Amino acid sequence: SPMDALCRVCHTASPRCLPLFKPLDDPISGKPATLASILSYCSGLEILEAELFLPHHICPDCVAKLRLSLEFKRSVHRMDRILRQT
Amino acid sequence: MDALCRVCHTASPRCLPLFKPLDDPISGKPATLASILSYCSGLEILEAELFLPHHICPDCVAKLRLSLEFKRSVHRMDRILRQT
Ligand SMILES: [Zn+2]
Ligand SMILES: [Zn+2]
Image 1: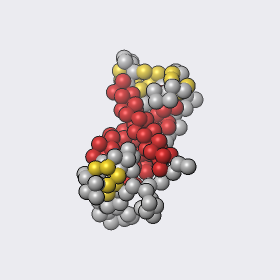
Image 2: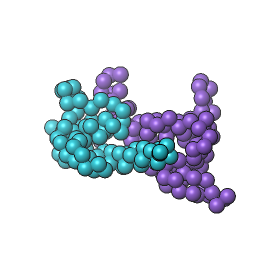
Image 3: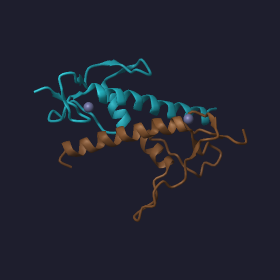
Image 4: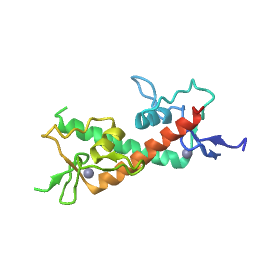
């Protein structure tokens, strides 16, 4: 239970929750992607490290739904660009 | 030629119409596949743009349903977290 962190999406306590604010890439222009910037992209919510009293992690099942959401949103945008000659 | 999917551009004789009213599958409230797609993607899916596809294939509708369930779950938890 001290072994556990709470998921920002479903509030489950899991010892395998992943940190929302850890960089997943090291890009040369601009800030790294994080699970929080992907969650914000998919959900439209502000997911900000500065709100220190909210959950800062995401459980493996919610990360799985997030990955599908991201692929879907990116596919909708990619097609929209192609269709608009963008 | 079969109808083209707005999301993946497959031509399918089983594509579904974006602009026909149905009940939102989470809220039960009036919606269309276009208003749900717009809500999940952040793009305007408007019938008046007559040069763009007006249909969506059953595979992309399945991904859309998962996307909507996920977005609504994130928002429901946010309300609980910020709840009076
Ligand atoms: Zn979760
Ligand atoms: Zn499709």
